[PDB]
Amino acid sequence: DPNEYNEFPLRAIPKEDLENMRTHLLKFQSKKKINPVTD
Amino acid sequence: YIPYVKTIPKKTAIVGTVCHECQVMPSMNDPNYHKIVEQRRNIVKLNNKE
Amino acid sequence: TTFRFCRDCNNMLYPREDKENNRLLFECRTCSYVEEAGSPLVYRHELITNIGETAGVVQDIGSDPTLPRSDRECPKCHSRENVFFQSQQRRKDTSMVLFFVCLSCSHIFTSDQKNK
Amino acid sequence: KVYEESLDLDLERSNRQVWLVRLPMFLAEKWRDRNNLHGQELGKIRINKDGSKITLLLNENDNDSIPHEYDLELTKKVVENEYVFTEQNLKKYQ
Ligand SMILES: [Zn+2]
Ligand SMILES: [Zn+2]
Image 1 (tube, rainbow over the protein chains, first blue to last red):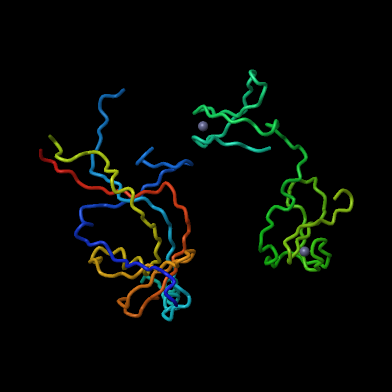
Image 2 (spheres, each protein chain N blue to C red):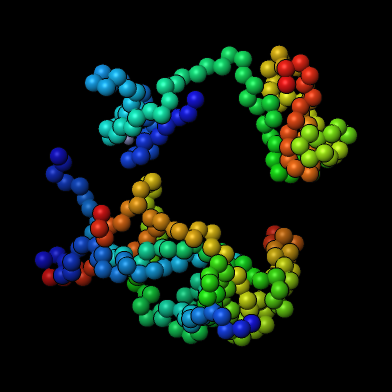
């Protein structure tokens, strides 16, 4: 294919910072737009 | 009000906001394709119990 | 009849009257959200109802092998293939009229010759 | 005195674009392993200039056992009210 695209590299997160830390998904259940930064 | 509530403090931080939801699906035009189909087929054909 | 739902909490609104303007308002019962009604109808109880006559019609209705076929003409695309079925309402008072679904345009027509 | 760190949620890195990706069983079984992810190259994300089509191509490290090309199907172009938050332990002295 021709170079009609902009592909960026993808690499895994180092394990040195993934230990003793848990990353979770937060889901607001509402019909509005909830944004803790401003709201 | 109630004087005591027994909270459990923890260190938390918001480290991103989801903007896209993606579903990774193997391309049907890939030369290695149909090997996953064989692997998927083998899932139902396997009997763990002895 | 159309049901309305609240914007701030998703709870359903209920009718209310405003004597100041003699108008119909739909107000929430928990968070005090109001919205003027677009129609004056708030209730309907159809003792004799025809809802559900063609219930179950999908984009792939013609793929069902148990449905019968017919050679009746489709009065929207002039096609002869179609699958017909009786009314899906199980009340023991409906007529035996047949509803025809075309396999070329997904158009639904009936064989009724009394009222249509 | 019990804790030597702030107990308030850190809303500083929230302005960070994140993609939620659902993986197949074969790909998820090797991408979720904690005995891996040494920072190596897991592939490249390719996006068309005009958009509407995305695909990630893996490297040749798969051992020629799984497809090297995958299509990223955007189940929700506009994802709303979903966030990612971490969890860490607090220093218990002073
Ligand atoms: Zn309300
Ligand atoms: Zn027709």
